[PDB]
Image (cartoon, rainbow over the protein chains, first blue to last red):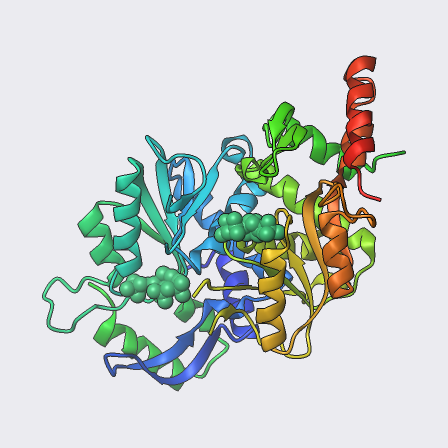
Length: 216
Length: 216
Ligand SMILES: O=P(O)(O)CP(=O)(O)O[C@H]1O[C@H](COP(=O)(O)O)[C@@H](O)[C@H]1O
Ligand SMILES: O=P(O)(O)CP(=O)(O)O[C@H]1O[C@H](COP(=O)(O)O)[C@@H](O)[C@H]1O
Ligand SMILES: [Mg+2]
Ligand SMILES: [Mg+2]
């Protein structure tokens, strides 16, 4: 019910650079969505610095212990790099020696051997889990141990409206692999941010979207 | 004959993390080289932050005006990202809105359209110019204008010892494309750094390598 400042700052910038837009949008399924998100619109030096900061503070706050930050090619490659750097810049002693790595689409791993290292997978978004599945395969081949994942925005929507469990995409992954799926923000945070920027009618109607499709 | 502090700091870290090593090494040609360089050993969060800083200060000092920083896949992708961020962090107002882009090995450009933008190509190293050639092709297809390139270490060696011109690899490129090829350091800087860390005999013998193969 409160937003951390890093989450405020992220969301403010996402809306200003138009990475986050509000309106009527259809997903692949065909489901109405009241917003569109494209992390790729964090595309300047100022914006990428801000994004790095946001991911790094999310990570620091989670208290996850890891050795390597891994980005799935291609979009995870820059995110892994800029985040690794920011963690060493803002995280103190414990984050100086974190490594990054990523895969060539076709060894396959660019970086120090992953053997016996604890890996945090970073990416932009997750839906069906195909990039997470591929990273797990590549990482487990190199004898790494995945301890977590992080994405920018957790849509916090049920994968299906017939699933009784009502697992979201990040929940699905989290269950299957037994690891946390962190995010900078979720749908709930976007809603809290909008308090007093939108009308009561608009507030209602988004707080109703949360009801029909919100996970669990 | 003086080293900027950023160049000192770079070289100190390169030697400590073993990205730069001294000894006897053979190139592909077969030529003796008195060192080995592997930028990929800047592989921690602290080291990548330092590398970002080094490239960004080199760029700032050059006074080159550009709009986009472009990294050739794969190794240029993280370098472009971390450098773009650092430029916005340390460069002031003029560097806030710089964009980055890079190519998929197989559109091909990830980032905002390059049409009418001034591009700085960033990579780790250059020898025959194959990655520069490929970037020029991709960039000129997208109507971008390349205004420069930067690499980490300029080996400052003649490509061939039969060429009368005695052009180095970066010089060759610079001539063919009509653009500056910047670097964080060159062979001359490595030599200046070593003053008083190595013996007179070792100083002589490296200052002799400079004579037989040093460009121009
Ligand atoms: O990162 P690219 O080189 O652009 C390839 P792709 O578009 O597959 O990548 C996107 O989808 C992935 C999500 O997978 P899923 O939606 O099945 O969870 C995630 O990695 C995004 O970058
Ligand atoms: O960057 P990678 O995905 O590892 C591919 P590659 O090894 O071709 O890349 C290396 O060579 C390029 C130099 O080219 P030349 O030596 O002909 O000037 C430069 O881009 C390096 O990253
Ligand atoms: Mg991806
Ligand atoms: Mg390359």
